[PDB]
Length: 229
Length: 229
Ligand SMILES: CN1Cc2cccnc2C1=O
Ligand SMILES: CN1Cc2cccnc2C1=O
Image (cartoon, rainbow over all chains, first blue to last red; front, side, top):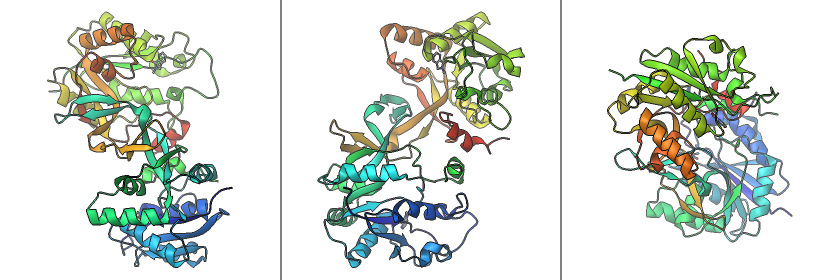
């Protein structure tokens, strides 16, 4: 019995001006934009209560997509940083009838290769967790720590090192307090787990697939061109 | 004035039997095998004294390549592990007239995107180094350390964490002693830097390009299909 969950897709930071170097979320991935394929990983799930995309109010690419005329996709105003945009998504969820104890999933707009297995695996393993968790994969490259002189001080034991992926799964109320307080404190928030970690909580690690990659360079598109359907 | 250097390409571990899931070094990369493109990064360098490929004596793919009939490529017998094959490559270099103080470069057979810039940058920055070093790139993914309960114990400060790449550049005599003694000691050697680290030396880090990737899955080929010429 998988739990019910809301979904927040932070996708702001896009300028008002179309550019030849398009935002990675609007690149073409086998006939569709990256963010459209990212939304498909969630929109069809029976336990989905509602999905909210965080966007700049002057985003020139979004009104061209068919998901902009979709009742299954809600929109929230972007913030100054990613954490602020996630915060506005949490406020938008509260307007749609979300409760403080509802599960919320935050997922990168440029991670379109999220499989149904990883999603349900994350949902079934955290459904009874006291704080939540996130998808992650073990580090497979040799890690080396540097001293101040640029020389190797040690080879890090990567058997305990995991790469942080998305989605990340936390309770709406707790994440709301953690994100808002950490922004007031001046914390260098990266993901939602870092805000929960600063607040004292230890998120659970849920192993996911390694090909759930984030599109950071247009060369990373080439890895996923054969991944659909 | 770049220093003179020998090159060892460990490429053993290949079985005697051709298989449909070919060894990654023999996959096609825009009309040529991965290992052929890897050798091209070195064979044309004016400071190259000699290149040695470590191969199993029953390798069914190598005799089909034109580099098997090339005077510019020498061959050494593979060992039981990668470190042993590297060791036999060092012995093969000594037969070709190498000296104990000569620079040796060890590079992965499945890293064909090594640019001339990274190679010379590694050579010019380590030419006067007391031990040597290796190419590396800074970690750009969020790193999380796991406790014994599978929960995040800390987010690792990745400002001091580097991913270890190749080539790696060490003196022939020192690497020979470090590799041989560490194998006798029972050390879990990964790369040459780990053997030098166990021997007490601190290798220098030389920043290289991030697209000098190792081909571990046939999906990684897709990243490099547009990288040549
Ligand atoms: C994914 N991102 C990046 C960013 C920068 C600034 C404001 N919002 C955002 C957001 O949602
Ligand atoms: C690159 N590799 C892997 C391996 C396994 C066993 C023996 N030699 C080798 C070698 O050179």
